[PDB]
Image (cartoon, rainbow, N blue to C red; front, top):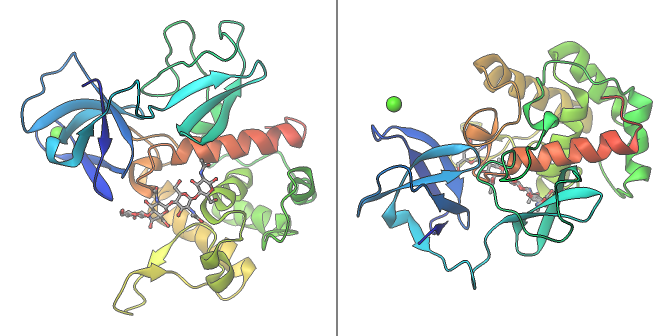
Length: 273
Ligand SMILES: CC(=O)N[C@@H]1[C@@H](O)[C@H](O[C@@H]2O[C@H](CO)[C@@H](O[C@@H]3O[C@H](CO)[C@@H](O[C@@H]4O[C@H](CO)[C@@H](O)[C@H](O)[C@H]4NC(C)=O)[C@H](O)[C@H]3NC(C)=O)[C@H](O)[C@H]2NC(C)=O)[C@@H](CO)O[C@H]1O
Ligand SMILES: [Ca+2]
């Protein structure tokens, strides 16, 4: 088979030494890499920029003519990644090399057979500040029809977090938008937790971390991302080969999803970044 799907809740990706490189989510589709040796026990695969090996035990072969395989498609304005059969995200502007409504396939979302994608927000250094002011960030809620968000009118807190921790506020808004449904998930509302941060406050089971109010949620999560990711050499969103996506999320397209929200916000606010 050319394509395999991840069966367990997560599965590891290994190098040729058997060292763990990363982990990917249930349902993720990986490509067989025909330039490297596979055997009965491990397949040479590629996913989201990462070339490595996976245990056959963790995979199911697909038939691309009846099973969903992720693909990319242009509507003539933007290029969309179908990350699931019923869900697409805009990743880039249309290029004249793209045929409208043709499905295109890629192991990294940058290299295609007839064109090359720039995904600049996917690789942007997150320690550089956004050119958007607090008042401009606050406008995004009306421009994208985001109702009932706990992050409404918190642009000033995102820009404070950026000033103090040296982390891009557009990234902070986009990450909280993707991770918490714009501060509307149950964990956002219960716990002012907009970035998916977990903690054992000694409390036996792993749970979402509690923050005392919306502002302390934004500032506290920024501190946690600075200390756990930025300060440890994860300084861009990236994919399964490099950046925050290697460790932050099993979803191979978490970084692409956040970059897509940054692209949409930047377009709505006049393209200053
Ligand atoms: C098509 C589209 O745009 N879909 C959107 C959804 O993606 C989105 O729902 C959110 O989806 C993300 C994944 O993209 C999901 O992220 C989970 O976040 C947790 C952290 O809270 C990660 O936990 C990691 O677990 C591993 C162990 O497996 C740990 O080692 C690691 O330390 C953990 N990370 C941290 C920081 O603690 C999960 O791996 C990760 N899950 C996946 C599958 O990647 C969010 O939880 C989703 N949020 C929801 C559902 O509210 C949705 C909502 O905005 O919008 C869709 O549009
Ligand atoms: Ca190694």
